[PDB]
Amino acid sequence: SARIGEVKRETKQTNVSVKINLDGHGVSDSSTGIPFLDHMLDQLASHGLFDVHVRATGDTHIDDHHTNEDVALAIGTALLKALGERKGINRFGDFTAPLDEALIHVSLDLSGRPYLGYNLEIPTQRVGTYDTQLVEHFFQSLVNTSGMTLHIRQLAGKNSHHIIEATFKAFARALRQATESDPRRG
Amino acid sequence: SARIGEVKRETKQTNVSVKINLDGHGVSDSSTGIPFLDHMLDQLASHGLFDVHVRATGDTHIDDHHTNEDVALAIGTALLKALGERKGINRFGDFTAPLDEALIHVSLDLSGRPYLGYNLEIPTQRVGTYDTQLVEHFFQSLVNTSGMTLHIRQLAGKNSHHIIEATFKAFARALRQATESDPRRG
Amino acid sequence: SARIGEVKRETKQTNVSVKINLDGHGVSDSSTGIPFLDHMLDQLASHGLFDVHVRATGDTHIDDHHTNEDVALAIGTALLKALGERKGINRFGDFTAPLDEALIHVSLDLSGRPYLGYNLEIPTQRVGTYDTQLVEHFFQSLVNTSGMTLHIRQLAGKNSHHIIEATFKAFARALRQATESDPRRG
Amino acid sequence: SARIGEVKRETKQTNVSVKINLDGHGVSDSSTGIPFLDHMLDQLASHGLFDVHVRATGDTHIDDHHTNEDVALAIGTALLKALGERKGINRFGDFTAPLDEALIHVSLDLSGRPYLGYNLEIPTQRVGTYDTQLVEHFFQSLVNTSGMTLHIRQLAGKNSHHIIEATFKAFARALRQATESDPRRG
Amino acid sequence: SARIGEVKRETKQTNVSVKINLDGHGVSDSSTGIPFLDHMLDQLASHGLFDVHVRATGDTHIDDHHTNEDVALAIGTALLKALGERKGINRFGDFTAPLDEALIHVSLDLSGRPYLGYNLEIPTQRVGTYDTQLVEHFFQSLVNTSGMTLHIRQLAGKNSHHIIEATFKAFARALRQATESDPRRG
Amino acid sequence: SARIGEVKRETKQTNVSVKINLDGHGVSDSSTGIPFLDHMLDQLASHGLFDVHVRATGDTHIDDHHTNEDVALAIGTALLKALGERKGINRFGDFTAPLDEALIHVSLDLSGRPYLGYNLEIPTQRVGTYDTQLVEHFFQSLVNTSGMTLHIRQLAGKNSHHIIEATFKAFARALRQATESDPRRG
Ligand SMILES: O=P(O)(O)OC[C@H](O)[C@@H](O)c1cnc[nH]1
Ligand SMILES: O=P(O)(O)OC[C@H](O)[C@@H](O)c1cnc[nH]1
Ligand SMILES: O=P(O)(O)OC[C@H](O)[C@@H](O)c1cnc[nH]1
Ligand SMILES: O=P(O)(O)OC[C@H](O)[C@@H](O)c1cnc[nH]1
Ligand SMILES: O=P(O)(O)OC[C@H](O)[C@@H](O)c1cnc[nH]1
Ligand SMILES: O=P(O)(O)OC[C@H](O)[C@@H](O)c1cnc[nH]1
Ligand SMILES: [Mn+2]
Ligand SMILES: [Mn+2]
Ligand SMILES: [Mn+2]
Ligand SMILES: [Mn+2]
Ligand SMILES: [Mn+2]
Ligand SMILES: [Mn+2]
Ligand SMILES: [Mn+2]
Ligand SMILES: [Mn+2]
Ligand SMILES: [Mn+2]
Ligand SMILES: [Mn+2]
Ligand SMILES: [Mn+2]
Ligand SMILES: [Mn+2]
């Protein structure tokens, strides 16, 4: 049956619930209190064919940082849980996706060793109300709990929304590849 | 008994109440009308083991500047009052604390001569709704009324929230050291 | 009697009322819909000893630009009206004022020829909700309708609020000097 | 009556007595054990029309530093005391004075917030037996206890005695302006 | 009683056993098949007062890399286990230690978030038979499984053995501080 | 009982007597014929809680060099003697202390191998009558006879007296730490 991982975590700052199906149909059901992040999690579901269910609340009066971080941490853990024994999967993923003028290359390995390589240069400080420093932190936190090797390379781009969104498209497609069955490893 | 300092000050712009216990247990009770500052004052309490009670209101319609300044001024005065005759204390504090990639070295002396040395380079203009120029002004104002020699050195950091928060962790730990009894000066 | 100038102007975008007494006592009564500008107009009154009455409404949904501009234009006209025949006045003003680390030199002549020389470098984009580009535009518009020669020189400064506020202090003091009676020109 | 401030302070290192009349006639009566400093305090009295009475002794065997510092601290306190409630005064001062080729601009505000901006470049290490590093320290210490905002800008100069002396002339004249009654604030 | 963590892990490449006592007496009992690493683990025990028991074998015919990595991973896990609920500890550590001309500053937080900041510049490729690239990898792997925030700053140094050994001295002393009881958090 | 070291040495150039108590109460009793050095030795006693008794005479007609050197040599020997078998001590010390704008980091190890790392940049040639080249020589000579590893790093500073004095404060505090009992090495 489908590989599903679920995490619930409450702290004094945030409360987060995540459920991810690696064998999904792109069902997008994310509400973090951070609308731009919800849009990116929808991208993860649609471009990766994951089913993504996220609920979070938190101390957004301070800033979006703790919520963003705790959502990412929980997603990484949910991915780890869903992966189970990791038998028979491709393990590696590699994809370069555009959004108009933006072009982002993502390469990853479900290695069990956390590492983020990241060189995005996002030229504005806010996309809507979303602090663009939080993009790197989202991926770093996700890597840290999932135990993923992840490289994100900005090949082109000028519009901040395009850069970030193309990153999520490429990541989702690379992660779909990595999590799928390898037909010669059954 | 415990060294407690209290200040109340009302101006045409702000109204501030501060009570600080140098011999506290980290009781955090700060409401300034500036949520990010409240978070940093919680850090001061938790990392310093001060009991910190702050209430402020002010002209935040203009910007957070007058409130931030008047809170800092009052805290410096409250620290001065709490210190009393300053007998038997370590006087000096020195600590370097991280928050992830950020690393901040704080050195201080409860000297009676105000000085701020500060080289933070905070790469974004807003953390939540908090103007990052206000960090330096908070420490400068606090130094001016407390009569503290304070040096803040940014050794590493990229995320603005991490840089500022690590600064408060390091400051709190250095100030705890300085305010504690020196076992050989009794 | 006192030199008073009054202007009312309604356009499709803004509605502005200004009354200025050159021989005032620093009565501050400004409500523009732009809180930071209200604070600066209070500075004008208090540091210049002008009585300043301003009411404005406008299309702040778009941005503060049209309101800021129309307020400034009306103030310049009100100053011109109040000056009347300009007999017996000092005409020239010259003052350098600080606000903490900021230091601003203003020199002006009530010449009848508009000119703004301005070299402020305001290092952040927003003070509260006030767009810092609007400072230069305020002075330019005021100069244009008053027919003033005005030079503003930033000698020092780092905090944007301090830079802008010191500018208004220096301007107010220079304008007080220029508008006052010359004891040898009666 | 005249605004007079008096300070006496004895430490293990120095003994200092200061009496300053803000409403003086330039009576110069300074003996610090540092002859060049006595000359500068005479300049303060003569160019500011303060009456300045200073007596100091100290550990000049070590160097002039502690004496210079403690004299400056006491002067700042005496100024603060003499100012009293600060009602009706100009508050701000601004003057540029030469001594031959030297030209020094001083701007100050009796603000209650200490700040020194200082860019003198004194090209020799000793004027007589006076260590030229002590000039900055004199002004810094004075600012710290008086709660003054003070900016000192070297516009020209080559001879060290001229640079330092012009600074005291300009400071004295700016401080006279700041401390005098504002005829419209009675 | 004493906080002890134990890890055993066998892979196709290496076999590692670690037992660490956080409340030790500096008992040094390390045999990794990598003599220079054994020397550094002795330093960890002696300078940290940890009891350190390590046994490892592995594919040193290929190079020391897999053994070094797997030892480090296991040590990080053993530290995590030994820490237990982490109640009442200092949590943060900060120390700068020399070895002759080498001087290394280590700052760490037992945060639960892995991060390594590292700027060593080791000027030779081999210390004995030990590949000096393996130093960074040892700390990175240890951080990854322990969930430690760790910064290592080379302040001075020329001799590779001195640089690496001073790093272990400083790390051990910082980790001792972090793991010890905070007398005010009981 | 208290760890006391005493040295007497007469040469054709100087005559020096030193007695140091590592377990002192900050008793300061130094007379070298070099007043600035006496002030620094008082700092050593007060900031380190050493009891420091020094008497020296010498050929100060030539310059202060031989006296300064011979005092330092004797102090290093006295420290070595007082340390005795060096059992149970912390051995390492690490502290960063300010004096106003100056900030100096000292790290040391009572290693038995002499080394001085020193990067002070003292911007004037004389503090009082004390030749500022003699600061480095004092520490070098002390290191050479004590067998100490000592690093002195200037992090900030402009006033020569402040730079040198902060160095002695930091050194004294680091040396107090190194010489004190380690509670876990009894
Ligand atoms: O690539 P998708 O099919 O998910 O479509 C993306 C949308 O165009 C949208 O999110 C967008 C287009 N430009 C910025 N954002
Ligand atoms: O160090 P603390 O125990 O006070 O925890 C701090 C929190 O992690 C939090 O304030 C934070 C983490 N990243 C940004 N902020
Ligand atoms: O100079 P004033 O007496 O008008 O006082 C100004 C206030 O201190 C205030 O507007 C301010 C201080 N720092 C930023 N703003
Ligand atoms: O300007 P004053 O009237 O006080 O006269 C100053 C003197 O000329 C004197 O102090 C001087 C001239 N050159 C260096 N010093
Ligand atoms: O600092 P320790 O007491 O552990 O002694 C270290 C030894 O001197 C030694 O490991 C060494 C000295 N130079 C390189 N290595
Ligand atoms: O830090 P201490 O308590 O020893 O006080 C030092 C004195 O202020 C003094 O030595 C000094 C202050 N500025 C230069 N020297
Ligand atoms: Mn974070
Ligand atoms: Mn989109
Ligand atoms: Mn301010
Ligand atoms: Mn935080
Ligand atoms: Mn316009
Ligand atoms: Mn203001
Ligand atoms: Mn000083
Ligand atoms: Mn002269
Ligand atoms: Mn590897
Ligand atoms: Mn060795
Ligand atoms: Mn010599
Ligand atoms: Mn001194």
Image: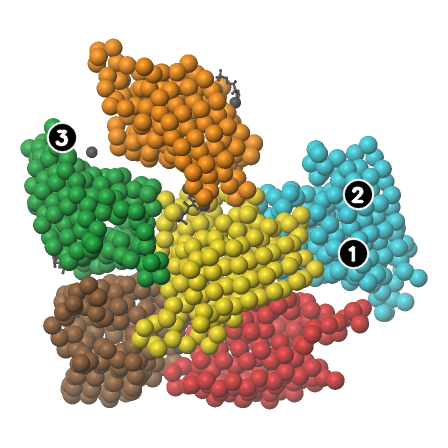
Chain colours: A orange, B yellow, C cyan, D red, E green, F brown
At 22% across and 77% down in the image, what residue appears? Answer: F22
Position of residue B166 in the picture relative to residue F13 (left or right): right
- Position in image of residue C173 (x %, y %): 74, 61
Residue C81 visible in image: yes
User: Could you tell me the amino acid type at mark 2?
Assistant: Ala
**Crowding near the residue tagged with mark 3, few <14, some 14–19, many ≥20 C-alpha atoms within 10 Å:** few
The answer to which image quadrant residue D115 occupies is bottom right
The answer to whether marks 3 and 1 mark residues whose Cβ atoms lie closer than 8 Å is no
Chain of the residue displaying label 3: E
Q: In this rendering, is residue D107 above or below E145?
A: below
Q: Nearer the viewer, residue D123 or C1?
A: C1
At 45% across and 17% down in the image, what residue appears? Answer: A27
- Position in image of residue C142 (x %, y %): 77, 47
At 74% across and 37% down in the image, what residue appears? Answer: C66
- Find disc 2 in the rendering and name its residue: C56
User: Could you tell me the amino acid type at mark 3?
Assistant: Thr
Q: Nearer the viewer, residue B152 or E171?
A: E171
Q: How many angstroms separate mark 3 from mark 1 (CA)? A: 79 Å
Q: In this rendering, is residue E149 above or below B115?
A: above
Mark nearest the camera among 3 and 1 is 3
Q: How many angstroms separate mark 2 from mark 3 (CA)? A: 76 Å
At 74% across and 61% down in the image, what residue appears? Answer: C47
- Find disc 3 in the rendering and name its residue: E11
Question: As drawn, which residue projects farthest toward the top?
Answer: A183
Quadrant location of the C terminus of chain D? bottom right
Residue C110 visible in image: no
The answer to whether marks 2 and 1 mark residues whose Cβ atoms lie closer than 8 Å is no
Position of residue C61 in the picture relative to residue E97 (left or right): right
- Find disc 1 in the rendering and name its residue: C28
Quadrant holding ligand 18?
Answer: bottom left
